[PDB]
Image (cartoon, rainbow, N blue to C red; front, side, top):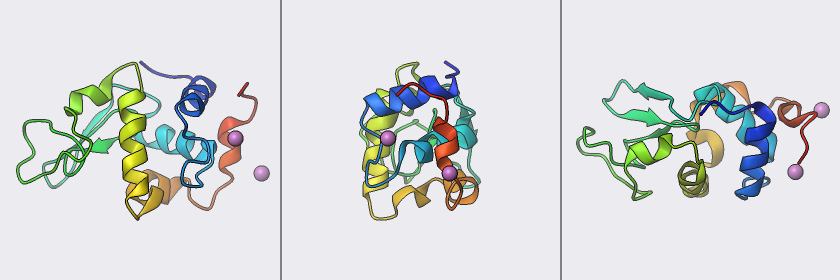
Length: 129
Ligand SMILES: [Pt+2]
Ligand SMILES: [Pt+2]
């Protein structure tokens, strides 16, 4: 599923991400835009052999089992393919564990390089929330 910007903002708000660990909703929308282009089916291979999955590009090095990432963890206790659903529940629940783990949204390279220190409120401008 390829979300519209405001549709994804609404879904993320419903799932409790607005100001989750102090990250405003525009942070999560900005992160999704530059991780996945709002596409739940997005997958990308990392240099280390792991893969990133779904709308928030959750990596198999730590967070999910994709059956092909040796010496990795599955801290969200999910098959990586769960993260590709049109339903963003699994990605959001796993993202809440990630962002809680001490490093905040710095875990998302696209957030650190493209969203952090920017006017992320722009990402939700015009949306019915
Ligand atoms: Pt808000
Ligand atoms: Pt502003």
